[PDB]
Amino acid sequence: KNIDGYFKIYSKHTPINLVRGLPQGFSALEPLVDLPIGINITRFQTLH
Amino acid sequence: KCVNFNFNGLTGTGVLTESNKKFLPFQQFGRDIADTTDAVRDPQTLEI
Amino acid sequence: AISSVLNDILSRLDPPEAEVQIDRLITGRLQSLQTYVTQQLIRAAEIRA
Image (tube, rainbow over all chains, first blue to last red; front, side, top):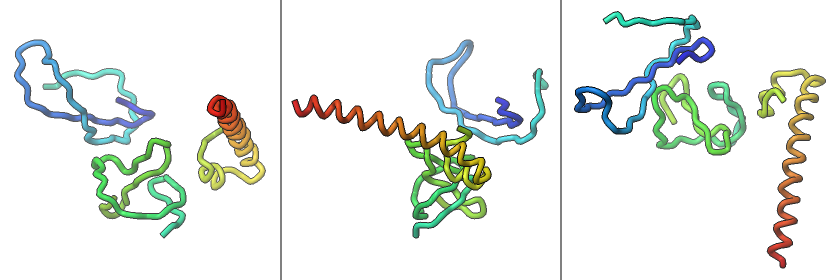
C-alpha cells in the first residue's frame, strides 16, 4: 500500500494444507520494510 | 527525573523510565488509550 | 484548529498568529468541560432523589 509517497511491506508465513481455494483460519500480518521512495505505480505484473 | 523531552517528533514533559514493554522492530513509538505519548525507543541505542 | 498539541503550535507559529489557533482550542475545550459539569449536575439530582 502506498501512503503519500511511502511503500510499506507486510509479510507473514505459516504452514497450511491446501489444494484449491482457501482454508478457514486467522493470521496477523507483520510489517517488514517501509520504502520512502515516492514513485506512483499504476500497474504490476508477475516476473516469476 | 521529570524533564522536557523530544523523541522521534513526540514532545512533552514527564519522567523517563525503562520498562520491559516489547516493541516490534518497525515501531519507534507507542501511545496510550488517550492518544498521548506513552513509550518511545531511542534512535541511537536499543532501549524501551 | 491546525493541531491539538500545544507544544506543536507554540514552537511552530508566531505569537500573534498562535493566539488565533490557541483560541480555537480553548473555546472548544470550554464548552466540552462545561457540558460534563452540566451533565453531572443533572445526574446528581437523580442520585439525590
